[PDB]
RNA sequence: CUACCACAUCCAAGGAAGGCAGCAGGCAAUUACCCAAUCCUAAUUCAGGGAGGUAGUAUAAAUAACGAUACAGGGCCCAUUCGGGUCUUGUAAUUGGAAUGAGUACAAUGUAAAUACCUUAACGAGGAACAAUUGGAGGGCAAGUCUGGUGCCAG
RNA sequence: UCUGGUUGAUCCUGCCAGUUCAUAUGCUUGUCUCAGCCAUGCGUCUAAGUAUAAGCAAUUU
């Protein structure tokens, strides 16, 4: 199993790698490097969109789920709040 | 002094696609 | 007192920004502009960046000249000549 | 050998905290005070100087008084690059060069932010309003702060102008501190055709003089129909006219445009809110919004029939 | 079970963070009583104080520090409900907040705005208290109104958030039991580490004093700048002992600390006082409120006010 | 499908300037391609 | 207002610590009584170097040159090129730049040109194997000083390229309460435009002093020639005592002047290192000013560094005094519980400094 | 109740007293109203009973039903291919009178009393805004932006 | 377990692609109906055994 038996995983957002990429809504824009809190293994994840990349910032808790090859994971919540809920402006991210 | 919540704040429907009225029933 | 003195200064700055917000925008800040709208030859004064459609024609400066003649000399030093021969 | 990475980080934090307490126990109470200072929970006396005359006079016990230490970055003033959006429950979008009462850290102030877009990351281009339902990059002048600091914005704080609407106008997070910005506005020149020879055409009203055309020789130009062209040469007669060769024949009704960009500057305006220094403490007023200003002087919103 | 154990362990993990709360003698938890005008902030505080210190404060002004446990103290501040600036700064310092909601009327602007301000400067512990429920005439509409309000409070604050319901006020006091029920919750609350609060020093003015010489006020005039002393308990990171530290006062400006000195505790916590599984002794419970009237004596400026054959 | 309704709003078309009303309707790429393709048909047939 | 100080003493330290603090500084009375008063060319050039890598700073030199007003900007960095005047080598400018490089908006990629060695300034290898390793201990993972060309005095002509790819928020908390064990001694004996025997003879002098030790001695025999050998002939040696246990290093360096015997200098730098070791507990005197500052700008935690009695001299005192006025931080010292030596544990707290100039 | 072994409280430090070393919780509201109903203890008809009782906190419906008028010729199905097959249709048009539920609620009934249940006056719909969601598949638009090209193209 | 490919066309063996009263998590409705640690809080009175209450009430008790 990708998470060693778990369905989801925590991680800490390290850097948004494609933030400098030119083409909007790019796959490279779309990738964020996240370090799993379980074991310290740094990995990368997909967001819902360049708008939803915009909620996520460094050093915030993020919930990961199975999904540029090499990236198998999708962020589903940030700081205990659903990204889709934030994207629909149905909720506000807690700091 | 008392100011009540408007419709948008009372529902938080957010941004949703327009849906045809036959979907209601 | 000092605090109200600063308030008078702030009030002065308010009234100036008050007038500018309603004053007519400068030709540079009106977006679309015609030669009549802006002062004549104003674009000479202002530095404007614009794209060029085609490759610029080169300038044969000296450094280009030494570089070209170097390659000519190396070709003849090696006798590496691309010329036609009898078949 | 710890089971999970998490408790390792917790172990390191606890080890440092355990290390810290051991030596302060070793330091003397006065020597501890000289080093750590006044720890939390201590009841302390703070004496201040040059406190304004209105504070002591206009003291209402019902209103709290809050003191917060400032780090070196907090003291410095400069341009703050912020990612901002109109609050979802705010009725109306915000405007560039529009006053906004902004709360960073321990301090509240009114500034004139410039709302901008990366244009897909070639340049920082000024934007006239906030996007309806997404963030945007915002530049304003004021005291600096560490990045990743969340903030919030309001347009009205006085009770008189509260009304029934939501007052939280903007929400955002700071991303950079520096003491300028290089914001630019896009300025296009529009000229008009009067003589057409297939691809080649003569244009007028683009420029007042051949002085201008010579600088823009070879510059990219397009018409509203999207046909690309170039400025080939300035015609000697009449003054200001130039010849253009186009990708395909243009028609007389066509409008040719040259795309260009003009720099924009951030206004250095600062007006901290000092409600406690006022008798009311609830009717603080600063720079007014453009809409209210026109209402006060009885001016209609500018409009152009062509636009 | 392994799949279950993995998921529960998944939820336990968090981002590592350092809490700067001192290991000994921590400050009281700041309780912000925020609500729209007229919801019952004052009657709540009076009810909340009585259950602890056994004495009614007929008049409350400014922060009110009270003992709540053997090693716990609370500082009650009502938020001025008509001032937005007052909601902003309290949101940045309130460790706990009591949110007054008029059940009959419903939510208001001043409520959720604080939640958004609190949501935007670091969410503290948020507790909703519902009031004016006796105004309801039918039980069916009361329960339906309660259900709608509690669910909406779960949208702003984590689902399952604790929401209290208060019926009416008797003798300026809420029902004891519901007032007693909230006692246990507040006592057991643990507070998450906030980034802003754990990195900077801050302290709430318990009392206010002007130290300017009266002679200077006359020979130059009132216009002269005033030397002021402000007292209180320190929070967050330690404040450096050397004077000259830069500090901001909300609604005032930036000043430099001219002098700093530590004073003994005005409201010594029980475990601390006796030091100098067992229930809190009622002697140990103490209330310290400089600006407010405690007992019958109220002090303002330099004048003090109290309530109260041989006669010839 | 992650596009909002607002993101897909109409962008309206501008018209000829009033000062230029006498020169005819302001044309667009969609109108231009019609003349461009038809001119090419003329030239191709004329070429043959 | 401006924290006001006297003389050219610790000039760079007072600019860089000002830069790290963001607190503006005034330094006055620069050689007031000298025949040539005011700032000299090299320290004017240094202020230009600060201006290049800082952004928004204000620098005011007086009419007579005897007073400087420095208002620091944010450390931004970028790629640049600096001309080092012939008075001082590149080493004079790279070391104070190492104080600032990890804490910038952009990576420091700066080319330094001029003389590369002197009798009083740090050589390349002193920066390379002597101060840079301390940065690896402080959390600066990636940092390099690439040597393109050397220039020996008096004519110079050398080039060195400084790269600090590691940008970190603040230095890691220091914890070194033990006297590190040295595992081996390495070093570089260098020469320019002169026969290789000089380097070998230099190493010959070095091994003679140190062969009595029970260690492996491996000194690199390294000889410049050709276009990249500078415009003057010269030679110097740098010997480093290296501790592989906890990655600690102690180094001594000097260059040979006209008329000197390479064996004599190799003997000098060899016994020179040994003198440094006897005076060292955890870091050398030439590394102590480097180590203390990063701890003062660490996180809000007490860090422990062991220092020998010989290290606490006038240099340690004025240096500590300079830090206090800028940061208000005091370094406390407590004796070690051991009786074999009389070393001291210097306990310092970081000011909670953070790299706010970085894009997040 | 006595002595012994430990716990622990108040104090004027001279003594006194406790069984809570409990109970209930979390990893947080167990409360309020009664002896009426079935029963009982007593100097007893009547007193009392935290015995006991009362209250508190996956299953069927609605979001609509029926007409009239005006204006237009296209609407649909099969087929990789070309095309073939079929006929009362479209409205993103106007308009009419009826029905009633959620709610707003006067009562009685119900009951130790009270809540709830059942029954039942008046009011209660055109955006019937009295404004259920979730997911997916396609579009198209700018004097808008970017990238690569064999123009007017492609991504 | 089935479905489509791998042949000019079939059979067999392989390969490829699509094919839960289990667990977590998200949005909506829930307007009706319906179902080891924590100092965390905290007896008994009838006409019928004894009245001199300086208790009460009545007045002929």
Image (cartoon, coloured by chain):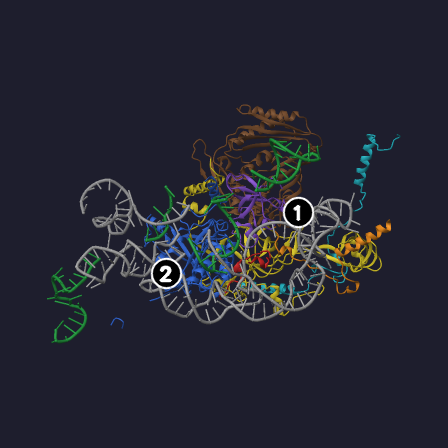
Chain colours: A purple, B red, C cyan, D yellow, E blue, F orange, G brown, I green
Residue B10, percent across and down? 52, 60
Q: Is residue D254 visible in the rendered structure shown here?
A: yes
Q: Residue at x 63, y 63 (%)?
A: C17
Which residue is more in the foreground, A55 or C57? A55
Q: With respect to residue G110, does E41 lie above or below?
A: below
Q: Residue furthest right?
A: C86
Residue E272, percent across and down? 36, 49
* Badge 1: residue crowd in 10 Å (few <14, some 14–19, many ≥20): some
According to the picture, the residue beneath numbered tag 1 turns out to be A22
Residue G182, percent across and down? 52, 29
Single out the mark in the foreground, 2 or 1.
2
* Quadrant of residue F31 within the rendered picture: bottom right
Q: Secondary structure at mark 2?
A: loop
Q: With respect to residue G244, does E18 lie above or below?
A: below
Q: Chain of mark 1?
A: A
Q: Which mark is residue C84?
A: none
User: If the image is split into quadrants, where does the C terminus of chain E sit?
Assistant: bottom left
Q: Is residue E61 visible in the rendered structure shown here?
A: no
According to the picture, the residue beneath numbered tag 2 turns out to be E175
Which residue is more in the foreground, D221 or A75? A75
Q: Chain of mark 2?
A: E
Which residue is more in the foreground, C80 or D276? C80
Which residue is more in the foreground, G51 or G261? G51
* Badge 2: residue crowd in 10 Å (few <14, some 14–19, many ≥20): few
Q: Residue at x 55, y 30 (%)?
A: G241
Residue G18, percent across and down? 57, 47
């Amino acid at each position: 199993s990708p998470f060693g038996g778990s369905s989801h995983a925590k991680g800490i957002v390290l850097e948004k790698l494609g933030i400098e990429s030119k083409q909007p809504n790019s796959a490279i824009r779309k990738c964020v490097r996240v370090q799993l809190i379980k074991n310290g293994k740094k990995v990368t994840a997909f967001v819902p969109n360049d708008g939803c990349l915009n909620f996520v910032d460094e050093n915030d808790e993020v919930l990961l789920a199975g999904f540029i090859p090499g990236v198998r994971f999708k962020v589903v919540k940030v700081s205990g709040v659903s990204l889709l809920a934030l994207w629909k402006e149905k909720k506000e991210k807690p700091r | 002094g008392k100011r009540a919540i408007n419709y948008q704040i009372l529902k938080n429907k957010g941004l949703t696609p327009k849906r045809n009225k036959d979907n209601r029933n | 007192s000092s605090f109200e003195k600063q308030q008078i200064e702030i009030r002065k700055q308010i009234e100036q920004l008050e007038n500018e917000a309603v004053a007519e925008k400068k030709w540079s800040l009106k977006g679309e502009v015609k030669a009549k709208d802006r002062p004549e030859d104003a674009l000479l004064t202002e530095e404007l960046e614009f794209d060029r459609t085609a490759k610029p024609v080169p300038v044969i400066t000296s450094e280009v000249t030494e570089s070209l003649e170097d390659m000519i000399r190396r070709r003849i030093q090696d006798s590496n000549f691309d010329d036609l021969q009898r078949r | 050998e710890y089971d999970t990475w998490y408790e390792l980080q917790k172990a390191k934090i606890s080890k440092q905290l355990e290390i810290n307490n051991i030596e302060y126990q070793e330091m003397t109470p006065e020597q501890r005070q000289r080093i750590e200072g006044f720890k939390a929970g201590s009841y302390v006396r703070i004496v201040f100087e040059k406190v304004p005359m209105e504070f002591v006079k206009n003291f209402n016990p019902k209103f709290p008084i809050v003191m917060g230490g400032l780090l070196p970055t907090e003291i410095k003033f400069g341009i703050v690059k912020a990612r901002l959006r109109r609050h979802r429950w705010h009725k109306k979008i915000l405007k560039t060069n529009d006053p906004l009462v902004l709360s960073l850290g321990w301090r509240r102030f009114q500034t004139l932010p410039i709302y901008t877009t990366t244009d897909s990351r070639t340049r920082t281009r000024m934007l006239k309003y906030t996007p309806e339902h997404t963030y945007c990059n915002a530049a304003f002048y004021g005291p600096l702060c560490s990045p990743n600091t969340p903030f919030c914005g309001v347009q009205i704080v006085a009770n008189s102008d509260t009304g029934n609407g939501f007052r939280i106008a903007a929400t955002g997070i700071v991303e950079e501190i520096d003491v300028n910005i290089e914001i630019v506005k896009k300025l296009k020149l529009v000229g008009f055709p009067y003589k057409i020879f297939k691809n080649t055409a003569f244009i007028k009203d683009m420029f007042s003089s051949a002085m201008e055309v010579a600088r823009f020789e070879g510059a990219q130009i397009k018409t509203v129909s999207g046909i690309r062209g170039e400025i080939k040469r300035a015609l000697s007669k009449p003054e200001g006219h130039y010849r253009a060769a186009f990708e395909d024949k243009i028609l007389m009704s066509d409008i040719v445009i040259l795309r260009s960009w003009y720099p924009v500057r951030v206004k250095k305006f600062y007006n901290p809110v000092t409600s406690l220094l006022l008798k009311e403490k609830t009717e603080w007023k600063g720079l007014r919004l453009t809409g209210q200003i026109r209402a006060a002087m009885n001016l209609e919103t500018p409009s152009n029939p062509d636009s | 079970t392994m799949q279950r154990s993995s998921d529960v362990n998944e939820r336990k993990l968090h981002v590592p963070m350092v809490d700067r709360t001192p290991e000994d003698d921590p400050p009281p938890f700041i309780v912000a009583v925020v609500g729209p005008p007229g919801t019952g902030k004052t009657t709540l505080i009076r009810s909340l104080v009585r259950r602890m210190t056994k004495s009614t404060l007929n008049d409350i002004q400014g922060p009110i520090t009270v003992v709540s446990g053997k090693h716990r103290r609370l500082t009650f501040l009502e938020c001025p409900a008509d001032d937005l600036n007052a909601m902003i700064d309290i949101a940045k310092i309130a460790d706990l907040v009591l949110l007054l909601i008029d059940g009959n009327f419903g939510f208001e602007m001043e409520t959720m705005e604080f939640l958004n301000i609190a949501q935007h400067h670091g969410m503290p512990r948020v507790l909703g208290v519902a009031t004016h429920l006796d105004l309801f005439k039918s039980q069916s509409t009361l329960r339906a109104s309660k259900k709608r309000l509690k669910h909406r409070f779960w949208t702003e604050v984590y689902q399952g958030a604790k929401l209290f319901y208060l019926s009416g006020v008797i003798n300026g006091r809420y029902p004891d039991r519901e007032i007693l029920n909230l006692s246990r919750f507040i006592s057991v609350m643990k507070f998450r580490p906030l980034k802003w609060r754990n990195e900077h020093p801050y302290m709430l003015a318990d009392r206010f004093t002007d130290l300017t010489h009266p002679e200077l006020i006359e020979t130059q005039g009132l216009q002269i700048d005033r030397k002021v002393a402000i007292y209180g308990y320190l929070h967050g990171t330690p404040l450096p002992s050397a004077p000259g530290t830069r500090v901001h006062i909300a609604g005032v400006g930036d000043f430099s600390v001219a002098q700093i000195e530590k004073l003994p505790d005005p409201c010594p916590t029980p475990f601390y006082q006796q030091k100098l599984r067992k229930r809190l002794d009622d002697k140990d419970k103490l209330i310290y409120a400089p600006m407010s009237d405690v007992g019958g004596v109220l002090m303002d400026k330099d004048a003090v006010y109290i309530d109260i054959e041989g006669e010839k | 499908k992650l596009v909002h309704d607002v993101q897909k709003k109409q962008h309206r078309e501008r018209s000829q300037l009033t000062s230029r009303s006498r020169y005819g309707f302001l044309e667009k790429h969609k109108d231009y391609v019609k003349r461009a393709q038809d001119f090419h048909r003329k030239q191709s047939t004329l070429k043959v | 207002k401006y924290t006001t100080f006297q003389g050219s003493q610790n000039f760079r330290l007072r600019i860089v610590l000002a830069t790290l603090s963001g607190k503006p500084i005034k330094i006055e009375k620069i050689r007031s009584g000298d025949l040539n008063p005011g700032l000299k060319d090299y320290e004017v050039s240094f202020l230009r170097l600060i201006e290049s890598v800082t952004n928004g700073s204000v620098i005011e030199i007086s009419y007579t040159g005897t007073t400087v007003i420095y208002r620091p900007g944010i450390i931004v960095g970028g790629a640049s090129t600096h001309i080092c005047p012939s008075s001082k080598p590149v080493g004079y400018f790279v070391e104070p730049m190492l104080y600032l490089a990890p804490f910038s908006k952009k990576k420091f990629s700066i080319l330094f040109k001029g003389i590369t060695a002197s009798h009083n300034d740090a050589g390349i290898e002193a920066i390379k194997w002597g101060l840079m390793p301390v940065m690896e201990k402080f959390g600066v993972r990636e940092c390099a000083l690439h040597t393109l060309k050397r220039g020996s005095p008096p004519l110079g002509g050398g080039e060195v390229h400084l790269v600090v790819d590691s940008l970190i928020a603040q230095p890691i908390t220091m914890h070194e309460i033990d006297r590190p064990i040295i595992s081996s001694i390495t070093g570089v004996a260098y020469s320019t435009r002169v026969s290789p025997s000089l380097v070998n003879r230099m190493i010959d002098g070095a091994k003679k002093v140190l062969k009595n030790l029970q260690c492996e001695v491996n000194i690199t025999a390294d000889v410049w020639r050709g276009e990249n050998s500078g415009k003057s002939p010269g030679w110097g040696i740098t010997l480093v005592a290296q501790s592989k246990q906890k990655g600690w290093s102690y180094f001594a360096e000097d260059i040979g002047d006209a008329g000197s015997i390479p064996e004599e200098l190799g003997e000098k730098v060899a016994c020179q290192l040994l003198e440094e070791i006897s005076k060292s507990a955890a870091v050398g005197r030439n590394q102590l000013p480097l180590a203390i500052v990063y701890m003062v700008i660490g996180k809000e935690d007490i860090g422990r560094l062991r220092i020998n009695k010989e290290q606490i001299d006038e240099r340690f005192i004025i240096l500590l005094r300079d830090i206090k006025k800028i940061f208000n931080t005091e370094v406390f010292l407590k004796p070690v519980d051991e009786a074999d030596n009389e070393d001291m544990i210097a306990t310092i707290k970081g000011i909670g400094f953070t790299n706010t100039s970085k894009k997040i």
